[PDB]
Image (cartoon, rainbow, N blue to C red; front, side, top):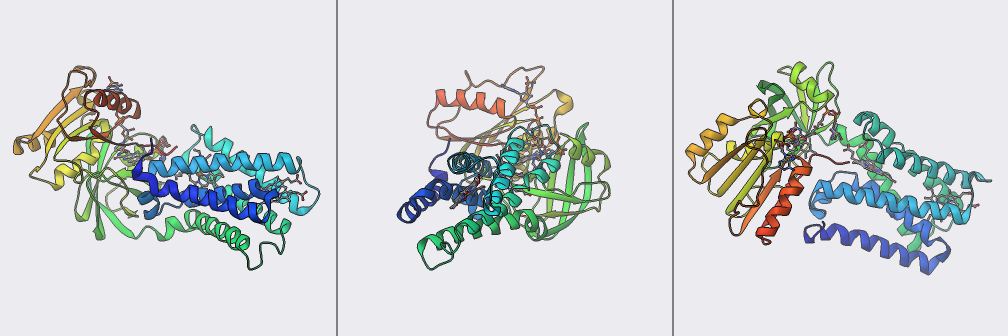
Length: 399
Ligand SMILES: Cc1cc2nc3c(=O)[nH]c(=O)nc-3n(C[C@H](O)[C@H](O)[C@H](O)COP(=O)(O)OP(=O)(O)OC[C@H]3O[C@@H](n4cnc5c(N)ncnc54)[C@H](O)[C@@H]3O)c2cc1C
Ligand SMILES: NC(=O)C1=CN([C@@H]2O[C@H](COP(=O)(O)OP(=O)(O)OC[C@H]3O[C@@H](n4cnc5c(N)ncnc54)[C@H](OP(=O)(O)O)[C@@H]3O)[C@@H](O)[C@H]2O)C=CC1
Ligand code: HEM
Ligand code: HEM
């Protein structure tokens, strides 16, 4: 659920829609609905550009891509009613046929984007990048149809041109420029350690210091023979200055390649730190809940804060003793810090993590990381006991 932490972004979108509606209604009322869809198409491209101001307005990157999907579905709904009320399956002029091609690509990509869970991510991304061709085709359709009406000195020309230019510049940056210029942190892998049968820890030495807060993540691009160079998001699992740690559990084809084939010395590139789950920014009393490899944001805090200044209760859940990581680190940290409580929950042995009879501290923030299904159940039970509790959760999926 959205809140005031994402109200700057929401007010920007409603300002974009209200201003577009007023500009069209006062100039060309017959084109309010196609005009509104072009603004939504512009905002969808902006919301996919991955800019620091984007997540500063929409709180988290998960909420950025949720709105990115909402403006995508609003666009196709308005374009379908544009096509239904203004034309047919195929157009008679070249200008109309450009809008026919664009709507076919827009509907085909949106259909594939939604029910494309089983496709490979890079194949999905390449298919997804066809909206730029449809977006360009739509811009030809608009400017061939409304010739000399959006190329004068008036409000409508400035409004249509600016949003069309912003979407054109946003689509070019993320598709052709983001992975080439927005990855300024060049580094190489120094040491690699296998924690358990399916998790590997990567130590990276960067040529320049990396600034991040515990609980934040980055995007990793590995440059090795036999490795894909696409960016994968990983939580920073420790390190300071020119040293970064990443803890990767085999989840698919790339993460199994990291476990088995990754070698020390391979070049890596980082873009910047993302994330709203800043542990240091929480209350004095904190509750940490981690599931499986969701412990990685909490390992950065433990490594970087040898003395704990907060009242932290840690609830770690793992699939038996064979799927637990950093067990000696957590035991050593609890011994050094009296104000740190460790609660190891073997799912097979102990059972389920339940907060019904458990008591949360008064005026405490709950940081939750792990499976989405397990987090939702846990978040519900905490709110019944103390509705004033502040709950912060980070997921591992954008789609
Ligand atoms: C904010 C965040 C933090 C994360 N932190 C960690 C971490 O500390 N440790 C860890 O092991 N994993 C972490 N992940 C998950 C990690 O990004 C994926 O598990 C990994 O990219 C899967 O690689 P694969 O291609 O082998 O998996 P696949 O089998 O190809 O993918 C399966 C799942 O991974 C997703 N996925 C695949 N490729 C990408 C990609 N390039 N970008 C985004 N999602 C992708 C798919 O949507 C699907 O849900 C994090 C994810 C997010 C969003
Ligand atoms: N910041 C981020 O976004 C980060 C994302 N991640 C993601 O975190 C995820 C964690 O998954 P993984 O490492 O495989 O861990 P698992 O899902 O395998 O284990 C997590 C634990 O949750 C328990 N659990 C599941 N459902 C419930 C429930 N309803 N109530 C209580 N306990 C429950 C399981 O016990 P049981 O066997 O009884 O179900 C299990 O021990 C990964 O998908 C990873 O990609 C990783 C790092 C950080
Ligand atoms: C008019 C509709 C849409 C447009 C114009 C659009 C545009 C884009 C673009 C250009 C990208 C970046 C591609 C790249 O990095 O190469 C992107 C990313 C993304 N889009 Fe869309 N999209 C649309 C619809 C959708 C829909 C329907 C979904 C449904 C899930 C979706 C989910 C995503 C996600 C999750 C990403 C993140 C990609 C990543 O993690 O690498 N988009 N979008
Ligand atoms: C400000 C935005 C827009 C304006 C002013 C506009 C204007 C028009 C006009 C006048 C027509 C009538 C076609 C004809 O001359 O016979 C038309 C048709 C159409 N437009 Fe647009 N349009 C806009 C946006 C879009 C966009 C962005 C798309 C597609 C992505 C689109 C898709 C279509 C389709 C499919 C038709 C039907 C073509 C046909 O059957 O002949 N429109 N538009």
